[PDB]
Length: 221
Length: 212
Ligand SMILES: Nc1ccn([C@H]2C[C@H](O)[C@@H](CO)O2)c(=O)n1
Ligand SMILES: Nc1ccn([C@H]2C[C@H](O)[C@@H](CO)O2)c(=O)n1
Ligand SMILES: [Ca+2]
Image (cartoon, rainbow over all chains, first blue to last red):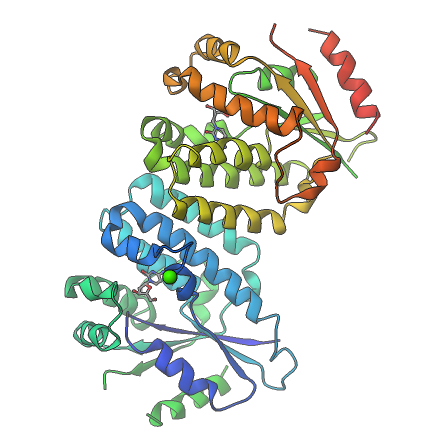
């Protein structure tokens, strides 16, 4: 009944800035940003910061928390307003896929998670979506493509204290998973429907010609 | 439509030996999957370095428990299902104690509870207990039964540990002074049996299930 699109992209690619521009267009368009605020406020502690400072200790914990929260937030917004509008479209800021096959996954491929952790993570992640996740099936994906050099430079522009330590080699590994997943679509997941899902890739390396393609996309959905 | 009872007790109190005599179906603790996570023992990992894997182990432990019990009761005349420990003992006894022992920081403990609460706010209402059987035993006895069972990981557990777990048990099942976030439990019947020392227990049990 409700068209669900996911906005994907590397760190600082411009996910949010795009999300916001979208909101101001159709009153039937709502958006669900990442609970990033909670991640940074867990009883006066920053679990996001805790992971960047000692990844091989809090990666598991942070990725568990991050996905759990995301499912809650999104499950919440699809049972809210817009649940009456003629053309109900909901934009998600990143999904439970990017969370597992990009960020989490990369952490494991960097020894920042042992076999025990990674095993548990996937076991957990699979179950979570096998229940209250089918309602979160995506109908499309918007890919915000940008060079890892641009993301690195945009990290300073946003000036988030925790992210200021991120090396290029890191954004480079995340950037590859992105390409390999939504560009060449060679990356495979356990959720087969995604193979049939439409991907709109936009070059955001450099403000209305994007709105253009977007509409043509949502219509062909 | 199905009576759900939970068998509670300290480590090595005799939970399983009692569960078997009872067998009415039973849902054993997922101890198996706990010791086998891709050729690794996450249970062993916790006892060896508690302040590093307590969180991870407790998250996994409860998740698995909910799964096992959920598919369990998912059709006879007198349907009774016995649970080997519950999601309560998991959070208000074991996990809880680990946090009261610095084996979990504020970050972990906060996340745990947040998670635990959500988990049962969904597919947990079907797991509401109708009663609880308390297997009471002295910490000294549990310690001695640890050797009798001879589980490699548990052989390092000191008395002070068992004693703590023991008090959380008494506080929660005998004294009824440990409040939780699941109020119905305050109305739930508790059958306490002294298992410190094999058919007189079956006796009380039946009288219990009838008064349910
Ligand atoms: N699954 C996720 C989601 C987000 N982040 C991080 C990257 C950014 O620093 C911040 C913003 O999304 O969160 C992460 O490591 N893993
Ligand atoms: N939430 C739980 C449940 C059980 N155990 C331990 C105690 C025993 O050593 C073994 C069997 O229950 O697992 C634990 O540490 N935490
Ligand atoms: Ca703060």
